[PDB]
Image (cartoon, rainbow over all chains, first blue to last red; front, side, top):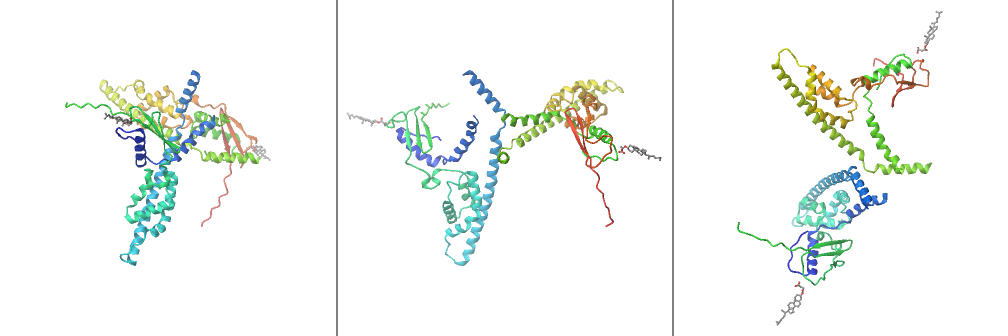
Length: 231
Length: 231
Ligand SMILES: CC(C)CCC[C@@H](C)[C@H]1CC[C@H]2[C@@H]3CC=C4C[C@@H](OC(=O)CCC(=O)O)CC[C@]4(C)[C@H]3CC[C@]12C
Ligand SMILES: CC(C)CCC[C@@H](C)[C@H]1CC[C@H]2[C@@H]3CC=C4C[C@@H](OC(=O)CCC(=O)O)CC[C@]4(C)[C@H]3CC[C@]12C
């Protein structure tokens, strides 16, 4: 991500970066890191001009080998698309059932809207299997909890949102602030920089914002002297 | 292949099988055998209830591994189709050039048809690269020789055949008799059978026709007693 700041201290710039991180950066997912580590561990489990020649020959031989990553990525994308379509159909059917239940409850009592909580309770099992399958295939089951899903469904029922709005929240990972408060931690943040944090921003300085299992590297650059002429 | 024979000796049945082999069976291609051996040699290079359990677990783990064969076979089929289309286009252009040359030679002298040999000489380089690429991708370069290709082109010019007829000879492997005489050997054939070859055919007897690098196993069965009734 890129941001524009003024004459500020290193600590102030780090705080601005942190506050923009929640609403800008995608939520951190350790599942991708675990998958990458599992993929990389195979090479470790299997195991200076001459060494350079040998590694160059090994790389050349590998370049002619089978491209295992591409086909499995394509299969994963196809499975994700199929499960997304199934989840969309299930959510549409659930919303149809919600509309039918509201219409039925309309005749029972006029001017007395039903509480959405019981409607969410009755409707959730219909799409529960599809939502769980989509979360499993997208590695998003940890963030989305059953109570959170029920609360979001009730909120959508109160607002009368379209099924697409409900679907898109669980479609892809988004900002940190979308999930619950306990998901993010604002206490373990640390600042690492060779220069003192009391000094102002300078061209070429680089600092790091550390936190549990992940760090953000911030590079500071000076805007070039723009020269404008009337043709 | 399946054939129907009468009361014949083992030698006569083997001779009938051999004479039908040339006009029925596809030409033997050792390139596929070499490819299969190269694929199988990787397992050798890499390397009783407990052993059975271990091999069953290994097979189960392999069943969940990547299907390398399918994607590479699909890529090979796509490449073969693309090269086939390119060869078809090249042969069509070559036949157009042949027709143009014949039309040009018509005005030079009436009633004196040109010899097809020089036309084949002039036309072969146009499609030579495409034909060589197709033979390389189909592992058929050994059987089809340059002189044989020229002779086939001259024969087609004399008969005025369509480009499809010329293409289909090199399209896929066919009968043994299509290629040159030196391709097939009718001297190294041998007969292997536990029973004496002088005896007649009997149900359940099996024999082998051996030849250089390849053998044909022949199984003999008796036609079942068919009972027919008028409803
Ligand atoms: C005759 C009298 C009126 C003279 C008064 C002198 C002031 C104009 C000087 C004396 C002390 C100076 C301050 C001493 C230390 C600091 C901290 C210093 O902090 C930094 O370098 C980090 C912040 C940044 O990046 O600007 C910024 C300048 C400042 C406010 C100075 C601003 C100018 C001050 C007030
Ligand atoms: C009073 C006179 C007229 C009696 C004559 C007797 C013949 C009717 C017999 C005597 C020798 C026999 C032959 C002896 C040996 C052979 C070889 C034998 O060969 C096999 O078993 C392999 C071929 C096959 O599968 O039939 C077949 C029967 C045959 C021709 C026999 C056929 C019947 C023959 C001519």
